Each structure stands twice: as C-alpha cells, then as structure tokens.
Amino acid sequence: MKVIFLQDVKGKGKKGEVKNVADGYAHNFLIKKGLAVEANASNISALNGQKQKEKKEAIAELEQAKSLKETLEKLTVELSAKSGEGGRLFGSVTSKQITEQLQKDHNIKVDKRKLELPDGIRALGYTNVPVKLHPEVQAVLKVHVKEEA
Amino acid sequence: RKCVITGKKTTAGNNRSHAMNASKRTWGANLQKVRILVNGKPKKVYVSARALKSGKVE
RNA sequence: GCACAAGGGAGCUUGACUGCGAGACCUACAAGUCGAGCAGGGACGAAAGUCGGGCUUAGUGAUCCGGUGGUUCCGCAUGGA
RNA sequence: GAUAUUGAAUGUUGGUACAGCUUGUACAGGAUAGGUAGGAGCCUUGGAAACCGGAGCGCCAGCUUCGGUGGAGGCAUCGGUGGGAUACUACCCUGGCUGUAUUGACCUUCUAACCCACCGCCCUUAUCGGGCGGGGAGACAGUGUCAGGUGGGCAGUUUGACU
RNA sequence: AGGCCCAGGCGACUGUUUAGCAAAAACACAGGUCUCUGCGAAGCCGUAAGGCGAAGUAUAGGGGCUGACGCCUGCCCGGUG
RNA sequence: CGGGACCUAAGCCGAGGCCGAAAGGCGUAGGCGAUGGACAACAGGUUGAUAUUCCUGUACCACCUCCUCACCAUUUGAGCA
RNA sequence: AAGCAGAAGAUGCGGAGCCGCAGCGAAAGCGAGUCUGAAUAGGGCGCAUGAGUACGUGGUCGUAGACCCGAAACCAGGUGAUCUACCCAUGUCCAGGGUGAAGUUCAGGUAACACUGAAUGGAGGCCCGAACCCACGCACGUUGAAAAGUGCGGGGAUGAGGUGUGGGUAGGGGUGAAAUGCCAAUCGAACCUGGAGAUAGCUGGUUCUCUCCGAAAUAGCUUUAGGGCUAGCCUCAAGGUAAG
RNA sequence: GUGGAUCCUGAGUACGGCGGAACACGUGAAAUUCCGUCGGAAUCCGGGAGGACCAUCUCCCAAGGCUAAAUACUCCCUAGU
RNA sequence: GAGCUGUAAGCAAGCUUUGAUCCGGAGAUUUCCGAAUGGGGAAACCCACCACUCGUAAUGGAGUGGUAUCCAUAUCUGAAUUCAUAGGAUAUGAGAAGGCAGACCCGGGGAACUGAAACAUCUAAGUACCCGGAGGAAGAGAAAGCAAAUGCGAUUCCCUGAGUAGCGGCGAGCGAAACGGGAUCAGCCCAAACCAAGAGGCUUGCCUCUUGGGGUUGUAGGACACUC
C-alpha cells in the first residue's frame, strides 16, 4: 500500500516519497520502526499543509532578505585609518572591521562569514566588497578608508 | 474458529470428481492469528486475510 | 437357374441417377423384400427397347450423444450472434 | 508445485518513463537509389588531399566509422545513367549496444513477520496459556484455497445366459 | 498317595488359546536377524488441540520374519518393491 | 466401630484457557474420589427379637471455664505455630 | 375453479380459466386444405360420411405402502467393560515335605592363585502334594437338578499366579500370548428407537349364491429362460351384415 | 416550487478466474443468487436487468434497516357436531 | 341458602339461617430435590463461611438472610514495566442458563433401504435424524421488479396457467414462472452531502470525534441560493 516515508529508503525521504511498499512488509517494518505513516487522506493533507507552510516560509525568508539587503548594499560606506609614507598602510581592515563599521554606522547586521574578504585590503582608497547575500544573488559594498589625524 | 471482524467460518459442500461422485467436503477459512487492536488493547485473535488487506490495523 | 446365356469376349459409357410410387410377400413390434408406372436430366442403341448395381439368396446392428457439408427454417424486447 | 499469510538487499534477463544511435545497391553508375516537400548551395586552422588501426555492416559490392599523423582545399545543381539525384528537418523498426527508477521471474545473503515441545520475570500457591526480556532458526515451516502422483488403509459396486 | 520299559515323529522348556465340540504338532516365549527413527524422534489415538513413545534419548524405542543349544542360511537383483 | 465434620492414587469434574460446522473435546488452578494412610473401650451380664450401642465396674481421645492450682511473661517480651 | 353471502349445507354471484367446433407442416407459414416435393404430377395427414361438453355409477390404469402377512440386510441417533478381553491404583491368598546352586568359612596343596574335599547357604517361571484355579479321559444327563452340570481319576499349585474393591478402552469401534476369540446366555461385525407398513421377478392365504360363455402350457424379443410386452386362444358391447 | 456554476446518493464491492450449492436447470450455449479462496470498477458525463454475448430501446438505483393484514399448527380451555 | 367433615360403608366426635360444605375473582403460605446457583453429591443426601436471633458459665447446638458462573455499568487497586495495561476486590442488575407439545419455522450439518427391474450420474432427499434461536404465528416484503402494451406498481396466500415450457445415463423420473381472477391493504426511518456547539490533534490554520438540525429519491432526488 501507499505510505508517507519519514526517513531514508534509498536516501532521506522526509518529503513524503509516495511509493508502493509491499503492504505486509510495509506495515510491519514502518510501524515497528516508525519509518513511515499510512498514506490516507488525513496524513496526506497534513503532509501537504506542512510542506506548503515551510515552502512559503522559506520563500518569504529569501525574498524579504535579498531585496533590501541589495538595495542598501548599493550604498557607500567609509571609515578612517592612519597611513604612512609611501602608501604603506599601518594595518588592514579585514571582514571583522567592515562588520563593525556596518553595525555601528548603518546597523546592517550581516554575518562575518556571509561577508568575507581574504585579500586583506592594504590600500588607502575605495573598493567594492562582494557579499554572499544569496547563493544565487550577491551585492557589492563600496568601502572606503582615509588617513586619520 | 471464525474471523472476529466478519462472519467468516468453515462451510461445507460436495466434492464432484470425474463421473460426478458426491463425496462430502469442507471449506475452510484463510485466517491467521495475528495481533490486532480490535478492543482497546491487542489480543492476537484470528482474522481473515481478505479482510486484513487494506482494512483494520494490525 | 443359366447354351433364346445369367457363361466367354470387342466398342461407347457411369442408370452403381434425383423426387416418388398404384399394389403386393413376410412379419407381435421394430425392421426387411419385389414393384409396373409419372416427372427432370442422361448413357447405350438407326430404331425398337434396356439401364434406379453385380444370375438370386449372407458381406451388417437401432436410440441417445458427438463431427462435417447445404438450408424460402426458428432464434426468450428490437437487429445480429 | 502456484497463491494469501510473506519482505530488504547483491548481482541477473525482457518491457515501460528518460534517454545513445544506426541499418538501405536487380542493373545502368564515378558509385550503395527508398521516396515524398522545401533545394542554388554547403564543410573549410572550431583545418583539404594522402596515410595508416580499430568498431560495425554486409546481397564479399564494398561502405561507413571512429584514433590519430599530414595539411588547403573537398562536396554540390549542372554533362550522361535510369522508374526515380546525392549539402540540412524527420519517419517507416529491415539493424546493436550503455546509464537512472519502477516493473515482473529466475539463482544468491540478511532479517521484521510466523513459529516455538529453549529459557528469566510477572500474571500465579499453576510443568495449561499470555504479556514482557533474551536466544534459535526464519520467508522456511504451519495454516486456507487449486492442481498433479501414489493410495484395497477405507467405502459403493460388478463379475451374463443356453446347458 | 506313581505302572513301567524299548524306539521314532513334533515342539528347546514353564506357560496361553477356539466361555459353550478341537488344549494341540497351534500362539507366545528368552535368542537371532533385517529395517525405521538425532528428539517437537519414528510409529500410534484424534477433524485440532491434547496425549502414548517417555519424567526415555541409537546398548533406547517401534515394524516384519525365524524361534533355545551344535554345523550352516548356497546362486539369481532379469521381474516387483 | 464402617464411613462422613481428616489426607490422598488411579479416574472423573474442572473458573480461566486451547481447540473445533454446531453439539462439544482437552486441560491449569481447585475439588471429588479407599479398595490405602492417621484415629479415643474392655469385661461380665440383660430381654423374645438390640447390643465391644443397654445395665454394672474400671478407663481413654478433642475442646471451653463459672472455679482450681503452681510457672513465666506483660516488648533479647510469655505463649501459639 | 378460487373466492364472496349462506345452518360446517343446498342456493345466488363469480366466465379468471379448460375441451371441442380445422387441419397440415419440425418451423416460417397456409388453410379444407396443408407437407413433401422443381412440378397443374404422385404420395403422407384431414373434410366431404359435424358432436362434443359437465356431472354420477361401474370396469381398468398411474402416483401414494396401494392385496394381506413375511425377510435376511442398510443408514442415522442413543445404551452398554455389574459377564467377558486388556490395562491402571490399592489390598489379600498359596496347609506341608524334598532337592540342593551361587556365595561364604575351614583343610589339603601349588612359588602364586589354578584345583580338590569338608562345614553354613537356601537360589529355582525346581520337584511331590492340600485350599484355590483350568478343564482332559471316560460314564449319566440332553422336555436334565443345571438354557453347558454331576461321579472317578487329571495339570498347575512362590511367579507370565489366583482373587476382592475402585477406575479406563463403546461398534465404520475397543480388546486380543491371535481362535474370526470376547464385547451382558446374541458377534465374519453388539443391543434399543426412528427412515419403515424398507424391498422381495419368492412361498402361503385371499370370507355369500345362482346363471350364460369358456382357454392356455404356443411364435419373436428380453442381463432372459419358474418373470415381462406384443401376437395366438377367451369373454362383454356396438356396427358390416351373409361375407365364413 | 424554481437552477443544473459546484458537492452527495450505501467499496475490498459490483463483478472476474478457480472448486461447490440452491434456483424446474444435473456445466450444458447456462442467465440470476449464495458460498470459501485470489484479482479488482465506475460512482450520474454513472451503474444494474431484460436466460451466453454485443449496439438500440425499455424498466430500476443494489452493496443500510423496520413493517400488522390475508398464511400454518393445537398442548390446552368454552360450547357444539 | 340447609346437609356435611371426598373416593368410602362406617365407629367416634364436631359446623352450620350471626349463615357452613360448595362455585368464582384477587391474595398469604409453599418441606427437599430438580437450570439448582455457598461446597460436594450415589435427586430428593452430607458439610461450611459472614451477619441477626434463641440457649449454656463456656465451647458444642439450633432458627432467618447473603455467599456459583458468564455478561453490562460504575468505584478502588492495578505486576512484568516508569506511566499504563492484563489481572484482582466491591455495589448495582423481574439479564441468563432449563423444557416445552411427540405440532407449526428460520438457518448449519445430513444419510441409507428404495426406483432406474443390475448400477456408479440421478431418484430416494435437503426426506428422517442431530444442532442453535425465538413468535403466536415465523420467513419474505415497498422494485438496481415484472413486462414488451395506448403497461402494472410492497409482500404474502388461494384457483388457473400446468403436468405446458424446460431439466434428464434425453432413462427412471423432476418440475416452473409471468400474465389473468381472488383473500387482505401501510408505508416508512438511517447513512452520504451541508449547518450550529464543543473535544482533541496541533493535519501549526487545517483534520476527525462526538450529540443535534437535515434530506431518502430515477418523471432522478437532496445540499446551495432563493419563493413558501
């Protein structure tokens, strides 16, 4: 008979991998182990409800996130840092410094892992910092640094 | 000896061989002693296979 | 019983046909046998006339149930099957 | 022996939903021509000619293919063939292969059900059984259906008449 | 309250049997032999549970044949199991 | 005294329970079941019928105080089992 | 007819329904014609030579037991192990005498037990023989005293033994040292009640009188030969009527 | 009473293969129904029946349930034949 | 309304016009066994527990009531196993076992003799018998029916159809239906869909679970909207 799998059959099937499972063995194994549940109207409707709920939740989470994140990321942000003779910067503003800047200036609250910068800016100028806002969408951040005192 | 769910029991009938002899015969029921929660608890009583498929839970 | 061939041979042929059948023998019944003659096509023979198996008597057994061919037949409402 | 109780695999042989493509001459012929439409053009350093190995086919005519060296030319309407012209879209299943999921069967190992006339506890002063917990096998066996073989162990009968 | 002896047949012996015709050369017997059975033995009773085997475990338990003891059980596995 | 207010074997009955068209069969616990086990009376007479049952003597078994008595103990506390 | 009203009735209603008047052909179908057949032919079945219907008596027939008695046997449901066969639990009985095993002790004796002889020994499905049990040879009984005995002798008589009490095996079965033996005087399949008034091609019996007539023991067939059908022979009634 | 935007009208069942039974019907071409196995539908734009089966037509909505009346019998009572 | 205490003679003794015997209606009592029910049981027998009562100085003894099993409700417990269950204890229960009449009826088993001149299909016959249930009747019953016409409209039973169709070693034998005419006369509820309330599951905004409102049909009906 038909069942709504709760875990892996040949791979995690929590999504409700409807199949035909040898009613005898199906009942015995799935019920003794909870591997699945009967595929009746009630359970099917409950699964559909939970699935659409989570789908819309994720859709909203991604939509709300991408839009304003990109829009604001299209802004300009600047800071100050001392520099020496010959353009040899005394330090380097890593991702942590940029995170602190965006947290204290504009209150963007982006993770230090989602926003990464390995090159370790050492120049006294402007630069665009890409961000991993979305696995399929990204935006740049116009960071700036200038001499101080 | 009968299915608890439906009135399935041992019936009787003839056994007509070649020449149409009329030896008497019995007809059993394909019932098994599986665990079912007919009442508030399981009891492990007899139940017919035809009724077991897509019917009461074991 | 057949020498007037029913016996021997030579030619053409398939009447070793189809529907029948007045009237008779035998028989408890079933059944069996002879049959002039009518019609449709024919064969032989110029014609007449013969041919509905062997010169005559044994060479075969029913009903039911099955199979094949033909049917102005019937065909569980109607038309088919 | 088949089926329900009674399924999971590892490989395995057909068919499905996705996919991979190739087989084609009676002769005429430069040849290997199946046609019906679009057809005056196509591939060329994302490389000609030639060269060689392997895969395939075959009406043993030969073709194609792919692996690559060598490298600037090859192909085509048009000249002739004959029933029908060669560059791109397709089919007719004539012809062989590999991958994913089901699909059903064959032969392999596991365990879930089924058993317990194996035990420990409780029900319970109980050598019945029945719930729990371990072990043993285990899709077996037992059980209900259908079929085949054997079956005087058993049952109902028959075994003629004249003389 | 025993008749005995000589000689042979049958059965090793004691025992059991056709109440109500036959007490025996018949039956059984201890012995031998073949065969089945690895334990939920096999066989048996019963439609099934449940029981005999057996509070047994291949020197133990069932089935057939022959019947102590001395010598031997010879050939044929074509036919049927 | 023979048996019942004492026990138990074979065997039967048998809550629950296991089986099985029905009826019903099997069986746990439990209980029945002597033909067994344990148990306190014996000696002389009496009438026409009864008598180790009646009469006359000596006795025994189980149990309770209205009393009787001596013992211990009333919480390493007598006593019962 | 059922049915309705009606004294359990007669009667009235009730034409639902059945038979005949038209038959032939399997059927379509046709019609005093129809079927067969190619066919106005021939032949088969009918009219043209119309009389049936509903009751009552009587004869006969078929179904019910069907003329009366008679089986052996079969099936179903029940009763029986108080007789007998076996088994289980628990008790009880076997008067007396003889034999003498194994073993044990001693003596002899061998290097050593082997071996021999004496003393105790009381084993035996042992012997003789009472009670008890079984009946094997002969007589009487066989309308007996007795629906299986008595009289004399006979075998066993401490292990397969006899026996009391209680219990189990119930018939398509049980039991059986095994004879077709026992299972309540019955057993090659116990007894009681039902199917059941089983069936009988078999035997026996079948009740008042007179009168008219008057046979057969033959052919065919037959799972049939002592049975049954047809025909042959008999009788009764109506016709042809003078055919024999 | 009016509309067919949309929803319902009795599922492991109607049926089918296998082995039987009863319907007058004996597996015969065998409808219809009940049975024990396995397979298993539509559900109104639908389904069942009209003696195999198919199309048209005709009739009706199963797999839910109840229902007195005319009908059979007399052990017994009252009265009478 | 004047003989009666039986059959049944009596011998004896008593009741009755304040009204007997007798007849009918409704009641009281009803030893023991028996489904038998506290346990056992060789039917009419024996042995107990708990309460109340009689009596002894106590036991001993005696009178009344309750004390079987299954099943329904409820309450307290509730082991393996932690909750929980199986199970155990308690109160309510004109609940229930049994035959009956040797009959009628619904269903489950289920023969043989017999007939076919044997006999196996068949008949005997779903007969006898056995089993389980109730009723005065039971079963069936309002068309997923008959039927083929300007068509009837729940079942049941009677006469016809009819010993016709048909079944059958196509034998023996078995055996209808509908139309038609009669006896009676009654049609109804549930599920499904939708709606009100609540409960649990969170099927997390959806699901089923329970009472109620609802509607029941083939010219299709109902829900839904509306007219009533």
Image: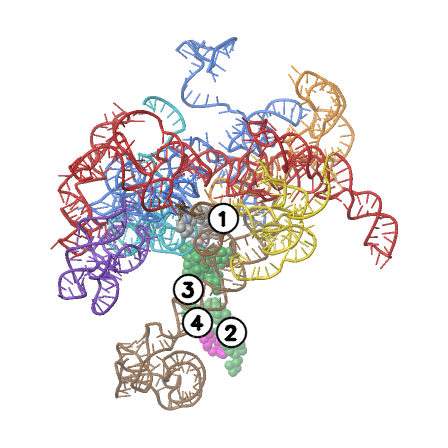
Chain colours: A green, C purple, D brown, E yellow, F orange, G red, H cyan, I blue
Amino acid beneath label 2: Thr
**Residue E66, position as x, y percentages in the image:** 62, 51
Q: Mark 3 to mark 4: distance in Å?
A: 17 Å
Disc 3 residue type (three-letter): Ile
Mark 3, residue position: A59
In the image, is C70 to the left or to the right of D117? left
Q: Name the quadrant containing residue G61.
A: top left
Q: Which residues are drawn in magenta?
A: A123-149
For the residue pair F21 and E52, the one nearer the viewer reads as E52
Disc on res. A138: 4
Q: Residues within 10 Å of mark 4 (few under 14, many from 20)?
A: some
Name the residue at 47% across, 68% down: A110
Cα gap from disc 1 to disc 2, whole angstroms: 74 Å
Q: Secondary structure at mark 2?
A: loop
Where's residue G127, x and y in %? Answer: 73, 40
Report the residue at 48% width, 62% height from top: A9
B13 in the magenta segment:
no
Please give the residue where the numbered disc 1 appears in the rendered image.
B45
- Say which residue label 2 marks: A94
Q: Is residue F28 placed above or below D42 in the rendered structure?
A: above
Do the residues bearing badges 4 and 1 touch, measured as CB atoms within 8 Å? no
The image quadrant of residue D125 is top right
* Kind of element beneath mark 1: strand
